[PDB]
Image (cartoon, rainbow over all chains, first blue to last red; front, side):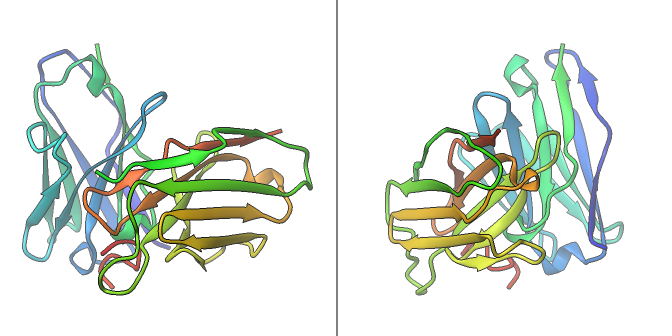
Length: 113
Length: 111
Length: 8
Protein backbone atom coordinates (compact mmCIF):
# COMPACT_ATOMS: atom_id res chain seq x y z
CA UNK A 1 0.00 0.00 0.00
CA UNK A 2 1.19 3.49 -0.92
CA UNK A 3 1.84 5.64 2.15
CA UNK A 4 2.89 9.25 2.61
CA UNK A 5 4.22 9.52 6.15
CA UNK A 6 4.73 13.06 7.43
CA UNK A 7 6.68 14.15 10.51
CA UNK A 8 4.97 14.95 13.80
CA UNK A 9 3.23 18.15 14.85
CA UNK A 10 5.41 21.20 15.45
CA UNK A 11 4.75 23.75 18.19
CA UNK A 12 7.10 26.69 17.68
CA UNK A 13 7.72 30.33 18.60
CA UNK A 14 7.13 33.29 16.23
CA UNK A 15 10.29 33.94 14.21
CA UNK A 16 11.68 30.39 14.27
CA UNK A 17 11.97 28.04 11.28
CA UNK A 18 10.62 24.50 10.98
CA UNK A 19 11.53 21.74 8.53
CA UNK A 20 8.82 19.22 7.71
CA UNK A 21 9.48 15.83 6.14
CA UNK A 22 7.41 13.45 4.03
CA UNK A 23 8.59 9.86 3.71
CA UNK A 24 7.02 7.97 0.82
CA UNK A 25 6.29 4.25 0.86
CA UNK A 26 5.12 2.03 -1.99
CA UNK A 27 6.54 4.14 -4.81
CA UNK A 28 9.62 6.11 -5.86
CA UNK A 29 9.28 9.89 -5.45
CA UNK A 30 11.58 10.49 -8.42
CA UNK A 31 8.91 8.90 -10.65
CA UNK A 32 6.46 11.57 -9.47
CA UNK A 33 6.17 15.24 -8.72
CA UNK A 34 6.07 15.90 -4.97
CA UNK A 35 3.66 18.65 -3.95
CA UNK A 36 3.14 20.60 -0.75
CA UNK A 37 -0.21 22.12 0.22
CA UNK A 38 -1.15 24.40 3.11
CA UNK A 39 -4.58 24.31 4.76
CA UNK A 40 -6.22 26.76 7.15
CA UNK A 41 -9.72 26.25 8.65
CA UNK A 42 -11.06 29.46 7.07
CA UNK A 43 -8.82 30.39 4.13
CA UNK A 44 -8.86 26.83 2.78
CA UNK A 45 -6.31 25.03 0.62
CA UNK A 46 -3.28 26.78 -0.88
CA UNK A 47 -0.76 25.15 -3.22
CA UNK A 48 2.72 25.85 -1.85
CA UNK A 49 4.78 24.32 -4.62
CA UNK A 50 6.18 21.24 -6.34
CA UNK A 51 9.52 19.45 -6.68
CA UNK A 52 10.97 16.98 -9.19
CA UNK A 53 13.13 14.62 -7.07
CA UNK A 54 14.74 13.30 -10.26
CA UNK A 55 16.60 16.58 -10.83
CA UNK A 56 15.68 18.92 -7.98
CA UNK A 57 13.66 21.39 -10.05
CA UNK A 58 11.14 23.34 -7.98
CA UNK A 59 8.12 25.50 -8.79
CA UNK A 60 6.49 27.75 -6.18
CA UNK A 61 3.25 29.68 -5.98
CA UNK A 62 4.39 33.35 -5.87
CA UNK A 63 2.88 33.68 -2.38
CA UNK A 64 5.49 31.20 -1.08
CA UNK A 65 8.59 31.83 -3.25
CA UNK A 66 9.90 33.70 -0.26
CA UNK A 67 8.69 31.62 2.65
CA UNK A 68 8.94 27.94 1.73
CA UNK A 69 11.85 25.87 0.48
CA UNK A 70 11.09 22.44 -0.97
CA UNK A 71 13.82 19.81 -1.13
CA UNK A 72 13.95 16.05 -1.74
CA UNK A 73 16.24 13.08 -1.06
CA UNK A 74 15.77 10.05 -3.29
CA UNK A 75 18.08 7.88 -1.16
CA UNK A 76 15.65 8.03 1.76
CA UNK A 77 12.67 8.49 -0.59
CA UNK A 78 11.75 11.60 1.40
CA UNK A 79 10.58 15.09 0.45
CA UNK A 80 11.03 18.12 2.70
CA UNK A 81 9.35 21.47 3.35
CA UNK A 82 11.33 24.25 5.02
CA UNK A 83 9.50 27.33 6.32
CA UNK A 84 11.21 30.57 7.37
CA UNK A 85 10.17 33.41 9.70
CA UNK A 86 6.97 31.76 10.93
CA UNK A 87 4.18 34.15 11.93
CA UNK A 88 0.74 33.63 13.44
CA UNK A 89 -0.72 32.97 9.94
CA UNK A 90 1.73 30.17 9.26
CA UNK A 91 -0.29 28.18 11.78
CA UNK A 92 -1.75 25.52 9.50
CA UNK A 93 -1.86 21.85 8.53
CA UNK A 94 0.78 21.17 5.88
CA UNK A 95 0.22 18.32 3.43
CA UNK A 96 2.57 16.52 1.09
CA UNK A 97 1.14 14.70 -1.92
CA UNK A 98 2.34 12.69 -4.89
CA UNK A 99 1.80 13.52 -8.57
CA UNK A 100 -1.42 15.32 -9.43
CA UNK A 101 -2.43 15.35 -5.77
CA UNK A 102 -3.49 11.71 -6.20
CA UNK A 103 -2.66 10.67 -2.64
CA UNK A 104 -1.96 12.84 0.40
CA UNK A 105 -0.09 12.46 3.68
CA UNK A 106 -1.80 12.69 7.06
CA UNK A 107 -0.52 16.26 7.26
CA UNK A 108 1.74 17.97 9.78
CA UNK A 109 0.09 20.46 12.12
CA UNK A 110 2.21 23.54 12.76
CA UNK A 111 1.29 25.93 15.56
CA UNK A 112 3.07 29.27 15.93
CA UNK A 113 2.71 30.33 19.57
CA UNK B 1 -4.20 33.38 -11.16
CA UNK B 2 -7.09 31.06 -12.04
CA UNK B 3 -9.90 31.66 -9.56
CA UNK B 4 -12.03 28.59 -8.79
CA UNK B 5 -15.58 29.39 -7.64
CA UNK B 6 -17.66 26.63 -6.03
CA UNK B 7 -21.42 26.74 -5.43
CA UNK B 8 -22.98 26.01 -3.10
CA UNK B 9 -20.57 26.47 -0.18
CA UNK B 10 -22.52 24.28 2.23
CA UNK B 11 -24.89 21.43 1.45
CA UNK B 12 -27.08 19.92 4.17
CA UNK B 13 -28.96 16.93 2.78
CA UNK B 14 -30.85 13.75 3.72
CA UNK B 15 -29.21 10.32 3.41
CA UNK B 16 -30.04 8.85 0.01
CA UNK B 17 -30.80 12.17 -1.69
CA UNK B 18 -28.83 13.28 -4.76
CA UNK B 19 -26.36 16.18 -4.69
CA UNK B 20 -24.85 18.57 -7.22
CA UNK B 21 -21.83 20.87 -6.84
CA UNK B 22 -20.83 23.60 -9.29
CA UNK B 23 -17.24 24.61 -10.08
CA UNK B 24 -16.48 27.69 -12.18
CA UNK B 25 -13.03 28.88 -13.27
CA UNK B 26 -11.97 32.39 -14.29
CA UNK B 27 -10.35 31.06 -17.48
CA UNK B 28 -10.56 27.98 -19.72
CA UNK B 29 -9.07 24.81 -18.25
CA UNK B 30 -8.74 23.21 -21.68
CA UNK B 31 -4.95 23.00 -22.00
CA UNK B 32 -3.18 23.55 -25.32
CA UNK B 33 -2.16 19.88 -25.24
CA UNK B 34 -5.84 19.02 -25.65
CA UNK B 35 -6.72 17.80 -22.15
CA UNK B 36 -8.70 19.53 -19.39
CA UNK B 37 -6.98 19.23 -16.00
CA UNK B 38 -9.93 19.77 -13.66
CA UNK B 39 -10.01 17.56 -10.58
CA UNK B 40 -12.16 16.88 -7.52
CA UNK B 41 -11.00 16.21 -3.96
CA UNK B 42 -12.89 14.78 -1.01
CA UNK B 43 -11.77 15.51 2.54
CA UNK B 44 -13.73 13.58 5.16
CA UNK B 45 -13.95 15.15 8.65
CA UNK B 46 -10.65 14.69 10.46
CA UNK B 47 -9.21 13.07 7.34
CA UNK B 48 -6.71 14.23 4.74
CA UNK B 49 -7.95 15.19 1.25
CA UNK B 50 -8.11 12.54 -1.49
CA UNK B 51 -8.59 12.82 -5.25
CA UNK B 52 -11.94 11.57 -6.55
CA UNK B 53 -12.10 12.83 -10.12
CA UNK B 54 -9.44 13.80 -12.67
CA UNK B 55 -9.62 14.92 -16.32
CA UNK B 56 -13.19 16.20 -15.75
CA UNK B 57 -14.84 12.76 -15.72
CA UNK B 58 -12.34 10.03 -14.77
CA UNK B 59 -12.89 8.27 -11.44
CA UNK B 60 -9.87 7.40 -9.29
CA UNK B 61 -9.46 3.85 -8.00
CA UNK B 62 -11.95 2.90 -5.29
CA UNK B 63 -14.30 5.81 -6.00
CA UNK B 64 -17.96 4.64 -6.29
CA UNK B 65 -19.69 5.33 -9.61
CA UNK B 66 -22.40 7.18 -7.69
CA UNK B 67 -20.02 10.04 -8.46
CA UNK B 68 -20.02 11.54 -11.95
CA UNK B 69 -17.84 14.40 -13.19
CA UNK B 70 -18.86 16.55 -16.15
CA UNK B 71 -18.44 19.91 -17.86
CA UNK B 72 -16.06 21.75 -20.18
CA UNK B 73 -14.06 24.96 -20.52
CA UNK B 74 -14.90 26.96 -17.40
CA UNK B 75 -18.09 25.29 -16.18
CA UNK B 76 -17.90 21.96 -14.34
CA UNK B 77 -20.23 19.88 -12.16
CA UNK B 78 -19.88 17.07 -9.63
CA UNK B 79 -23.00 15.00 -9.07
CA UNK B 80 -23.76 12.36 -6.46
CA UNK B 81 -26.62 10.03 -7.39
CA UNK B 82 -27.20 9.15 -3.74
CA UNK B 83 -25.43 10.63 -0.71
CA UNK B 84 -24.03 8.09 1.77
CA UNK B 85 -22.30 8.48 5.14
CA UNK B 86 -18.92 7.97 3.47
CA UNK B 87 -19.60 10.88 1.11
CA UNK B 88 -19.80 13.46 3.90
CA UNK B 89 -17.05 16.06 4.19
CA UNK B 90 -15.67 18.88 2.05
CA UNK B 91 -15.41 18.71 -1.74
CA UNK B 92 -12.71 20.78 -3.46
CA UNK B 93 -12.39 21.28 -7.19
CA UNK B 94 -8.95 22.30 -8.45
CA UNK B 95 -7.23 22.97 -11.77
CA UNK B 96 -3.81 21.86 -12.99
CA UNK B 97 -4.01 23.41 -16.44
CA UNK B 98 -2.39 26.68 -15.44
CA UNK B 99 0.20 27.15 -12.70
CA UNK B 100 -0.01 27.96 -9.86
CA UNK B 101 -2.42 25.15 -8.99
CA UNK B 102 -5.53 26.70 -7.45
CA UNK B 103 -8.40 25.27 -5.38
CA UNK B 104 -12.05 26.14 -4.93
CA UNK B 105 -13.04 27.26 -1.43
CA UNK B 106 -14.77 23.92 -0.83
CA UNK B 107 -18.32 22.63 -0.49
CA UNK B 108 -19.28 21.21 2.90
CA UNK B 109 -21.65 18.24 2.58
CA UNK B 110 -23.41 17.21 5.79
CA UNK B 111 -26.70 15.86 7.16
CA UNK C 1 2.38 10.44 -16.37
CA UNK C 2 4.52 11.93 -13.62
CA UNK C 3 1.62 14.09 -12.49
CA UNK C 4 -0.71 11.06 -12.63
CA UNK C 5 -2.98 12.89 -15.09
CA UNK C 6 -3.75 15.54 -12.47
CA UNK C 7 -1.93 18.52 -13.95
CA UNK C 8 0.00 19.66 -17.03
